[PDB]
Length: 290
Length: 290
Ligand SMILES: [Ca+2]
Ligand SMILES: [Ca+2]
Ligand SMILES: [Ca+2]
Ligand SMILES: [Ca+2]
Ligand SMILES: [Cl-]
Image (tube, each protein chain N blue to C red):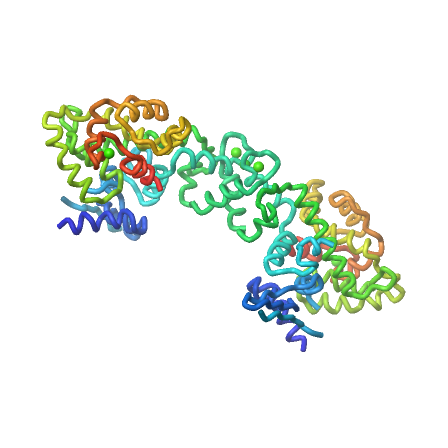
């Protein structure tokens, strides 16, 4: 029944946003004569963005998810908004914010979005999230980024737990799985690779959330990394553990533990020469953000 | 055969740009095994934008129109470009220029258009006209406006001539026709109105090009006019000849002759009370730019 595990990822890559929200959502609240509104839980959301008993629902005849207002619940319009935040890289937001900020006053408002919207013709659902429901709000690169991080943090924590950590730690294989799921890459090789982790790491104290988050923060800035290498005249250079740690530190301001690197090399080092070629890791992770 | 005169205006309002260029163009040059390229003359262009013996073409087996490069001839891509310039009001260009000018360096380039283009998805034919064929050019509100005026001047001159002026002058009826064509308004009333001009102006020394251009410059800023009235606490106020002349002067920096006003009042003053109500003139002319 892996034909399904596969199937579900196709929906996750190749499918209307509606088809997806609907497929992973578990709540359906009806309030006659109103319409049915479908809802996700935070866990429904996270499963919807990451591979590997009841849709319940209630009916009337007649953590930044609490932020949504629906008491932790997530509506489709929430889905779109969150989905979009998560998938909009800092650099992109920064330009787009630029072009929107018409008077260049460091902010962005409804009137301006208003104007720009038109000039486009000559993304309408998100307006309340950006400028409140009053629409008299003002959006800031800093605000938004602050928020993007919280969202990524909370989502990644939910993901961590989805592995049932023990005293704050998951296994190396569980971690390798998170990486492989993240890579969005399907290969028998890496798959065989990811299984041998528990054997490669027969002891394994595991990875704490901090260790895992640190690495995903690095994954978050993997484009900058390639720029950093090129700058030092080393474009497409193979990574060794110490070099990976130096860049992660330089372009993401984090300290990657030796153990994290151990696992990441053990999983991605497909030719077994001890270092990660561009095609083996950066290429793939760079690709994971289009 | 007015059923046609009518027909042709529908094409001019309700029709693919292609259908139009093709319908009014007179030249078709073929260079086997190349494709046929259709061409307008400057006069073909002007007729295409204004109501009321041979399409010739040559074939090989085997004034800002000279600016186009095709030696006065106008291609479809030229058509689009010119068409668009003519129909893009100063204020609109100014904002749109704003949002495009990303580094706010007073210019606009290919890289920037490039960036903005994407962010749009996340108007391709005009690129060479704006940034040259090298695309290394830079667009300026001032450049573009300078150009917009020349274009409007040259088009309006061509239109003037399309009435066979005598010693630099056309008739009041001919003028009234230009206004009525411009208004894009079809009514039996104003039509009856426009005919009685030669009788209302039995002498008539006529209108010189300067007189006509001055008024079309005013028509060009008719939105600002309504703003000017509102500002002085007179929104939607009826115009008398002297008031029309004061605003034309204030918001378009032109001196409208008494005679021009005479004709414009004689044509638009449908109730015959001697003054132009908002619905009688400004409303209509404001409307003529969406
Ligand atoms: Ca702003
Ligand atoms: Ca390797
Ligand atoms: Ca610029
Ligand atoms: Ca009147
Ligand atoms: Cl801007």
